[PDB]
Amino acid sequence: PMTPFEAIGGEQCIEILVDTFASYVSKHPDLSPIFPDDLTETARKQKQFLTQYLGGPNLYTEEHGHPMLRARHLPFEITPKRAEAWLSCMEQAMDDTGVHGHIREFVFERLALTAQHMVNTPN
Amino acid sequence: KQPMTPFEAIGGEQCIEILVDTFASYVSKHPDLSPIFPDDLTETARKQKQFLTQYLGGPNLYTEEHGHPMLRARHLPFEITPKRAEAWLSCMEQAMDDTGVHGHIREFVFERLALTAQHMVNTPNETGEI
Ligand code: HEM
Ligand code: HEM
Ligand SMILES: [C-]#N
Ligand SMILES: [C-]#N
Image (cartoon, rainbow over the protein chains, first blue to last red):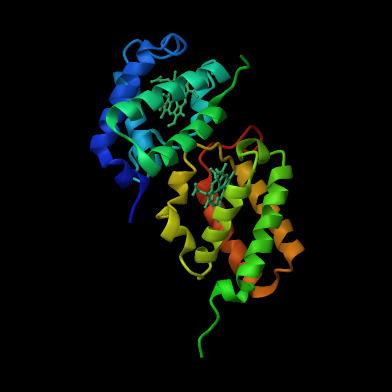
């Protein structure tokens, strides 16, 4: 024991985490313009990626191949301000789904680092 | 008579401490690598030492603290190109040279590490690399 995926609560917790996150993303002025109007598909892939990243089944790469995550974000203007907005929505999502304690810090530190890596545009 | 574990054969903790500290120095200077690593590699180095210790047959310091390495999953968000894997291995080679790691243990460790690096690659090659 115990993968971050099991510690965070498994599929059930990822489901609601990402559903709540997508809701906040869709309502954030800094993010809603660059995401799809319908985030269903986006959220489906976010669940895949977070699942596989945190030690669950290899959902994302089994369907979409190599993650190449920064490259998939290149077509979008991802500014430091937008990275902040993203993490701000993940923070609220984790608060709303009960993700606390060491797993919260573990996951958020790694997504904050990842979000920094996605930045491809100055403010 | 017990053969040495690979971790013993390389010189144990004192070697792994020196090798990783040296490696992380090269990493932080490598233009292909430093952008994606944290600015302060101290936590990364601490984890690398723990990983490599158990990776080579020492105690399970990494798994006991962090859980299963699952390194391909843990590297999923990071832009790991074939080039950056070679840079990684290049810094390890230089680090091994600086720390005195030679012989069968060096080739055993490097060849295993070269397999792991290739498995971390999660971004296609760039133009000219086909
Ligand atoms: C730094 C701020 C970020 C912004 C502004 C951003 C924005 C976006 C946008 C607009 C898309 C397109 C969605 C679609 O076409 O369906 C996308 C895709 C995606 N993003 Fe993010 N993102 C950010 C960071 C992250 C982070 C930290 C992760 C960590 C897991 C992540 C994982 C993904 C995944 C898995 C996809 C699906 C890619 C695909 O297969 O098409 N992103 N992102
Ligand atoms: C192939 C080129 C590689 C690149 C570019 C690379 C890059 C990175 C980066 C940017 C991180 C994030 C640092 C952090 O969050 O602390 C990381 C974490 C890590 N890497 Fe690598 N890596 C590579 C290969 C390897 C190899 C070959 C090994 C082991 C033999 C390894 C073991 C680790 C470990 C244990 C961690 C810490 C994960 C954690 O517990 O958070 N990596 N790597
Ligand atoms: C990406 N959210
Ligand atoms: C990884 N270093």
